[PDB]
Every structure is written in structure tokens, then in C-alpha cells.
Length: 113
Image (cartoon, rainbow, N blue to C red; front, side, top):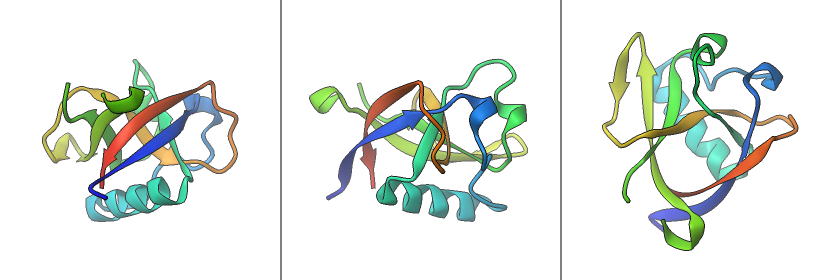
């Protein structure tokens, strides 16, 4: 399927144990996609002071369209030293590995895979 319905656990930035997916744009996009498939991916909502507490390169989920079955259609865009790899809509949050942190909420997304 070109799209997959996922429910992403929303984590508080201070709870996150593994603060990124790796060391290159290509690795973080690769790892983010694997974790999204394996149900081991969390979402951090971006506000003032969040991104400096996480590790670059960043992986964002961004709105790709204006929402089947409650699921917002999203795609992945990476960022490293202020350059983004991908073009998409508004940021829903930054992806991180999920290793058992308790979420505050769930974000229903339809991921372009």
C-alpha cells in the first residue's frame, strides 16, 4: 500500500531516551521509515526549546494534503544545519524512536510509504 494508517504515541521531549535516528539525512529517513513500519516510532510536538533538546538530523512529519478516517496524510522531511530534504506542508511534529516512554496522546496519521 502507498499509505499506511498509524497511531503515533506523542512523547514529552524531556522523557525521550533516544533523541534521534542517526547521523546522516539518508540514515534518519531510513530509520524513521523502519520504526514507523515496526510500530516503534514516537512523535514530539515542536514548540520553543524542543528542537535544541533533540539530535540532528531531524525527521519531521508534515501535512501532505487537506484526512481519511481521522488520519492526516503526512510525509517525511529531514533537516540538517537548516537545510530540508523534501518539500511538504505544516509540521505535525519531529519523529524519534519509541523505547517505552509513556505518551501524553496519540496522533492518527496516514503515512505516504
